[PDB]
Image (cartoon, rainbow over all chains, first blue to last red; front, side, top):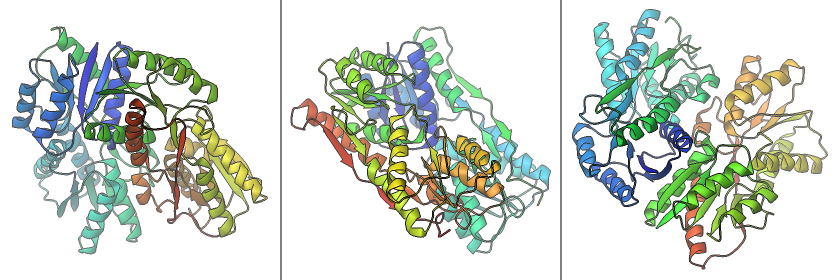
Length: 271
Length: 271
């Protein structure tokens, strides 16, 4: 038994956690895994990865790469009837997929800050080339609007701590000082926290911060980071079970949404 | 062209960075990669992984799993004449390998602290079940001894930030307060830094900290972490080039040591 995985760079935290879980579950079920890391940027790069995987005679494909509606459909077409499961797409795209609830994750972050009394909020989005970053940013805007709040600033990073530091420092140097920040992932949040601290402000007391992912490291940031938990292990594990069920015609044909939750720590307080 | 990789959990930072580089270089050279994640703990688990990889008809193997001398030799024997390259072993083991210079990494950390004037030093080692953690701990002791210093305490963690936090808090709660700490990796260092800070002390000014790896996140810890850079991308990239050369009988037959360097940041000051 052999399956193939087309994945975003494993140098990134989220992708590596998902693939680790995929490999663990595959081993458990007696399936070997061919892994192809996408050259990044573009549906063509992903199609090439899929082509190479099919050449290795895989009987199932897990696409752990961000794709918009049309591109995901295009990649599915390239799988040549071999079952394909997508893990980084919109839940509206008509393909087989499993993704985390972006509606719940963004609502949780916004409602948490609103409930604490925050009105001056800034957003630090992930790279908009990524469907996940886009869904997250759209969600923040949706719930902030529902709470009759317009953010005082919104910027874009690249998932790295340094981008969080740079974007936050640029915002602060501009004279824009929110009482709270919604950040696209924990690593960028770490960067934001450093920027806040080096600017002579207190994370939490002066500027609250909410991350996203609930990485193992987040519990030890200074101070511990309030974030949105995305159970990557569960996603990876479930993707293998699902793919094998699909390959045997006993699964389904559509999208599954996995729940997320708010992890309250030490970076969020009333303004 | 197809190669196989037996690897430690990709949930771990170092392994994921190495494998990412392996996949990138493999793609560049037109080689597909079958990846097997070891069930952890034991030479038997690694042998099983190798067996499954050989069943997929790989023509080369990269062993990215910690193995002592005898176990590495045993795993090599199990590769059935298929070229095998080890990335987590001692450089004294008579097999093909590429590892970072532990002698240089430990000397750099010790000499940096000694040069700053530190005499009261504590050690926080990685899990001793890992050859890398063992070589690192032995190295610290070697150079501390050469500088006529006996550490005031030495503990063991598990590579995670939480283990660094727990071990450091336990040390401090015991009344053992060093002026500097040598920590086995950046994540455990993050945990130590949190413990120090929550104990009412200043990282750097009160207790200096040196990490290991130079993770992307380390530049944004609070404060930025002085550490030892291990270029995982270079290691992964080089391992692919080396394996293919070995498969064509144009490489060598032995160990290569990759250099490391000290990255001075904000967590190390005179006592």
